[PDB]
Image (cartoon, rainbow, N blue to C red):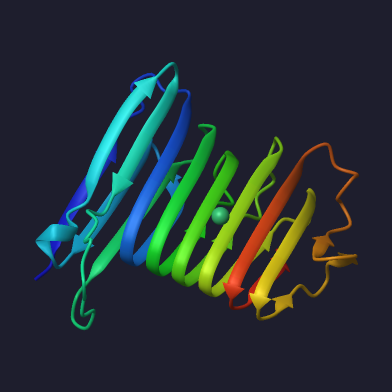
Length: 212
Ligand SMILES: [Ca+2]
């Protein structure tokens, strides 16, 4: 039986959330649908993977950090082990998210979050992100992957521009306007007051961009 834990964070004066996640291996799932700042359920089969949470409010910014203890490691055998983080985030508070993911699968619905910035690094694995919200300010998204696939869902209603670069692999961007070298946009870009600027880099793997 793996360990299971719930963690709940109240804002305690924060007016912005800065979420910083360091995740070595496994499955990370993020959504909205939380009343407090964040609620998470963490499942881990190895005691060494026990997540470490730090939260402080500095000058109205709630700095929330969640880290899987590094295994500096030689080998880890993954069969029959489990490491899963399932996180629910507040939908109203202005939010920046930074993720460093070693290996595994990252899935996030951020369409209901008051998102300002997202930075994702992934070593080996998959990223699937719904950032198709009607955001009420400009949004900056940076995604960088080593080996694996990244899929991003973007809104039709606000302007989007994506710079998508791969080493070896394909950019699948049907229904987007193609601009010169590695730039993709929707029809709203340049027209809506608000926009999402997206940079996506993949070493080896596919980049799939879709409107939703
Ligand atoms: Ca870099």
